[PDB]
Image 1 (spheres, rainbow, N blue to C red):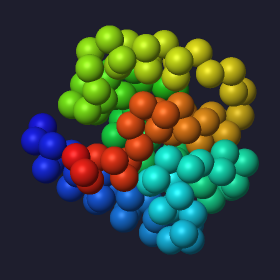
Image 2 (cartoon, one colour; image 1 turned 180 degrees about the horizontal axis):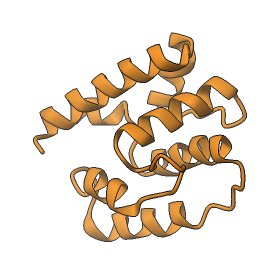
Image 3 (tube, rainbow, N blue to C red; image 1 turned 90 degrees about the vertical axis):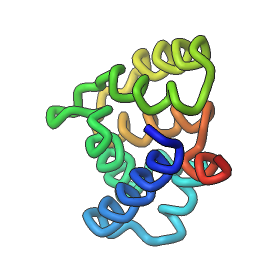
Image 4 (cartoon, rainbow, N blue to C red; image 1 turned 180 degrees about the vertical axis):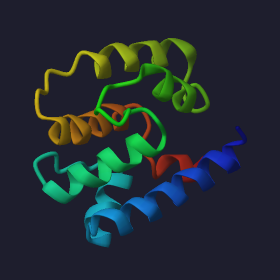
Length: 119
């Protein structure tokens, strides 16, 4: 959008979602750095919140590839985004909250939220 703007939007969404979930600052820092404790209830809620706020996840927890493509296209090369979408779209997680932390874990192997601050 401007990388400076994506960085700001990411900070805003991390702030709003931390308040909405009550996730500890340490656990939120771990998610931001790409160290996702997938089984943690508050990590799941925080991941779900960030994804829904970027419309990557719709209100029914339906995965929207357009949402993740829009974001990722600004950080990584075209073919890597295609690879990301294939990997992330095919995650076998039947639980929606566990799907959300696993989704953020999948995206994070390509680009962590913290890495965007470098940028």
